[PDB]
Image (cartoon, rainbow, N blue to C red):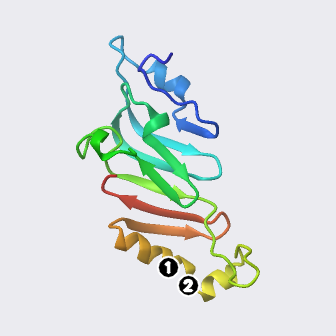
């Protein structure tokens, strides 16, 4: 059991500060509110939250989902708080391991020159814009697509 009632057990996921530290800074009333929160999943991506974040009683296992080229925060709209509350607020999302596929070999394309030639990052920048997010960058080395959102 965690002092703030925070639940995170999914393999590969982690938080910054860690779940251990989040407990320490929890008040005797079982509340946890930290500044600059990050939750990610090794090899898939991470979500950075600047400012104050109230983690009290949050079941991260059911709320945060970080998959290949996709992040979902609150699977069901019927159970998502209003903008500004919980994790339904502005954040910076990093999606790792994202690369295009060669039409012939069906193998991923990591070649920097090839990625430049097909303007893959511009393709990702356009997708971020169409969804209302603010593209920040694409790092070829790790296939890291970064962009900001107002909320989820």
Q: Is residue 152 left or right of residue 118?
A: left
Residue receiving disc 1: 123
Q: Nearer the viewer, residue 35 or 74?
A: 74
* Residue 109 placement (x, y as % from top left): 70, 76
- The residue sitting at the top extreme is 28
Q: Nearer the viewer, residue 51 or 71?
A: 71
Q: CA distance from mark 1 to mark 2?
A: 6 Å
State whether residue 78 is above or below residue 28: below
Residue sitting at 36 percent across and 42 percent down?
87
- The residue sitting at the bottom extreme is 117
Residue 3: mark: none
* Residue 37 placement (x, y as % from top left): 44, 39
Residue sitting at 47 percent across and 26 percent down?
22
Residue sitting at 23 percent across and 43 percent down?
82
Q: Secondary structure at mark 1?
A: helix
Q: Nearer the viewer, residue 118 or 72?
A: 72
Q: Residues within 10 Å of mark 2 (few under 14, many from 20)?
A: few
Q: Nearer the viewer, residue 125 or 58?
A: 58
Q: Secondary structure at mark 2?
A: loop
Residue 119: mark: 2
Give the quarter of the image for residue 13. top right
State whether residue 129 is above or below residue 84: below
Residue sitting at 38 percent across and 30 percent down?
55
Q: Is residue 135 left or right of residue 94?
A: left
Label tally: 2
* Residue 134 placement (x, y as % from top left): 37, 66
Confirm or deny contact between disc 1 and disc 2 (CB under 8 A): yes
């Amino acid at each position: 059991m965690h002092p703030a009632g925070i639940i995170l057990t999914k393999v590969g996921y982690y938080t910054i500060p860690s779940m251990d530290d989040l407990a320490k800074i929890t008040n005797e009333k079982g509340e946890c509110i930290v500044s600059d929160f990050t939750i990610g999943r090794k090899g898939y991506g991470s979500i950075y939250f600047e400012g104050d974040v109230n983690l009290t009683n949050l079941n991260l296992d059911d709320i945060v989902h970080i998959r290949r080229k996709e992040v979902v925060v609150y699977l069901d709209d019927n159970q998502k708080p209003p903008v500004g509350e919980g994790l339904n607020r502005k954040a910076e999302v990093t999606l790792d391991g994202v690369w295009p596929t060669d039409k012939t070999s069906r193998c991923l394309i990591k070649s920097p020159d090839r990625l430049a030639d097909i303007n893959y990052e511009g393709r990702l920048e356009a997708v971020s814009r169409k969804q209302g997010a603010q593209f920040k960058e694409y790092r070829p080395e790790t296939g890291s697509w970064v962009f900001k959102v107002s909320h989820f």
